[PDB]
Figure 1: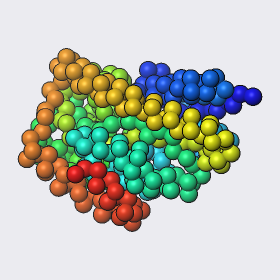
Figure 2: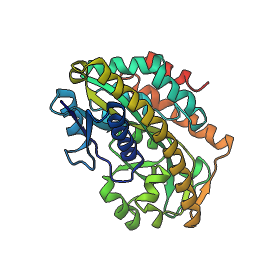
Figure 3: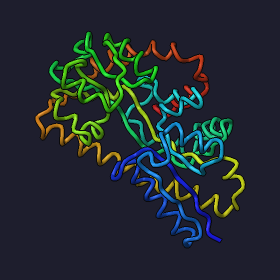
Length: 308
C-alpha cells in the first residue's frame, strides 16, 4: 500500500524553504512511482516550529523542519552554526559538502540520533546583515550605541552587546511597528526576508555584515525512519539531497534579487572594507567563549575546517 508521510514546517507559500520542500515532495513521488507521498503542512498548519519538531522527535508526526536557532531548544550543540563569523559566504560550497558528505555531516547525524531524529535536508536560510532606519552605518564604529531588535537567541543578544549595540528582543510581528515608531534604530536579518516583509519601506541603510548564519533543518523521526524498507529510506535520502541542490541555488538567486530590490528602493547598501570586516570579526570573537561549554570543541573545529 501507499506510505503517507507528514511534513510540518512554519514557512509561507513561495518562501525559499517552502519551495525546497515542494521539490522534495515531487522527487519522492517520482522516485517511488507514487508509492510514497509527502503531505506538506506549511505555514504552521500543524503548530509552531517548536511544537512540530517535538512531535517529530516523539513520533506523533513523521517529519518537521526547524530553523537552526530554534533547534537549540532540543540540543544547544546546534548553536555551533550561530557563532558570529564561524562561516562566511565565500566558503559556502565547502560547507555544504562537509554537511552532506563529510565528518561534519556524520557528527550532526549523531547529535540528531541522540534526540530521536534523522536529518533529511539542511535547507539554506542564509546570512543576516545589519540595517538601520535613520543612522548611516558604513563601519563597525557606526554600530556603537544602536538600539537593535533581536530575537530571543542568546547568541544574537551577545553579538549585539559585543558590538557596542543595545539589543532589544522583540517578536517578529512587533518589529515593523518598533522600527517605525523608533523604539529600535535597526535590526539584523537576510535581505530576502527584509524585502519580502517590506521592512525595506522603513529602512535606509544596510551593511553586508554577514554576522550570523542559519539553516532550516528538515528531520524525520528516527524510529520511523528505521522502520522503513531500505529502498524507501534511500528514496527519502536521495530526494532530500537532490532537492537541496536546487533549494541552495534558488536561495542564492533570491538573495541577489533582494539585494537588487534594496538598491532599487533607494537603500544604501555598503560593502564593508577588509578593515571594517576585521573589526566585526575580532569584536564578536569573545562571544564564542560565552557559549563553548554547550558547544563541543570538536564540532566547532569541524565547521571551522570548512572555511580554509
